[PDB]
Amino acid sequence: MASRLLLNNGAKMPILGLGTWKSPPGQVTEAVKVAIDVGYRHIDCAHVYQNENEVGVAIQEKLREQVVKREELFIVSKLWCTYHEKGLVKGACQKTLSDLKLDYLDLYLIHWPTGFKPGKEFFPLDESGNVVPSDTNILDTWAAMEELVDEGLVKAIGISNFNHLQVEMILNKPGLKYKPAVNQIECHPYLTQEKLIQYCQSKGIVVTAYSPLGSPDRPWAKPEDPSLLEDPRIKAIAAKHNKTTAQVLIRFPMQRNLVVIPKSVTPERIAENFKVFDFELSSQDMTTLLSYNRNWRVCALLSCTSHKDYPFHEEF
Ligand SMILES: NC(=O)c1ccc[n+]([C@@H]2O[C@H](COP(=O)([O-])OP(=O)(O)OC[C@H]3O[C@@H](n4cnc5c(N)ncnc54)[C@H](OP(=O)(O)O)[C@@H]3O)[C@@H](O)[C@H]2O)c1
Ligand SMILES: CC(=O)Oc1ccccc1C(=O)Nc1ncc([N+](=O)[O-])s1
Image (tube, rainbow, N blue to C red; front, side, top):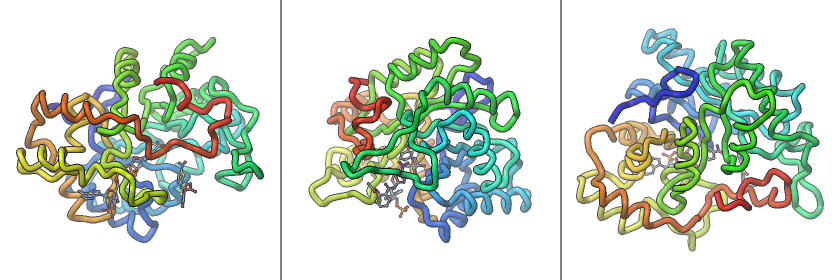
């Protein structure tokens, strides 16, 4: 097992990163500092997580402490849906850079394929509970992303929650300058993404697996919901390797050649989640974990099912 994957921009991306969605501003600074100390060199961020300033403080302090050099870190952020208009893309990126206190991002993703009405609401909704869309399309937004590479603001650009037809649309864009480097998608044993992964990987697009532990702190979690961390089949596999269930769930996408980004603000867990390079899941473990697929999504973007670019109508 190698620790980094080669992207189609020629850069290498650490296969393990720290997630920061739901990491409070008052805890994420310590969380990122601890991650850096124990060996994480990839942090997954987003404007919409409302904590990029506090992530940037942690990064800046570790650089000042000479713990790590900038070129050794791989920092990822994401363009929010209200900024899909070509004229707003650069300014959204610069705002993220200012918050993170960085000169450049290693990777900037379109967070969702769906553009939302521009303004001061992350999620403009109407009386039907549906999102107010913007007059944008993914190809024009992609063109604006491409300019950020030429302007040196980001080293790589990519997409998130795009289905394979949406990836194909970009790959066939008239005037395409840069292929997406990464498609970041939800992936875990209840949503195995076999076709979308095979598709992206066949195109040289690296897949990042999000919510690998099943996002147990997701704000919409219900007692009747399944739980990967408490799944007794997965506990059994973990017991066999003398590892925790979290460690199995993190190692699982790694062996499929995916990048994986488990989130924690707990120092012991941040350390524990990193201890995944000292064992291997067997071929049958992998086949068994894949058999648990139920196409069960934590992030289904249910407020946008009528948006023209809603990604989860298609099979994959
Ligand atoms: N592109 C997108 O649209 C998108 C969507 C969702 C997520 N993401 C990214 O993916 C990252 C990870 O996904 P996620 O935050 O949804 O959930 P996740 O990483 O699957 O799970 C996070 C939850 O698991 C807990 N946890 C972490 N390590 C644990 C361990 N060793 N044992 C027991 N519990 C543990 C955390 O608790 P504590 O924090 O309290 O320790 C937190 O409650 C996000 O933070 C974000 O960066 C991206
Ligand atoms: C359904 C709903 O309203 O869930 C919530 C309940 C409480 C607090 C926050 C959310 C929420 O939607 N948070 C998000 N952060 C990032 C998001 N993204 O990237 O799409 S959505």
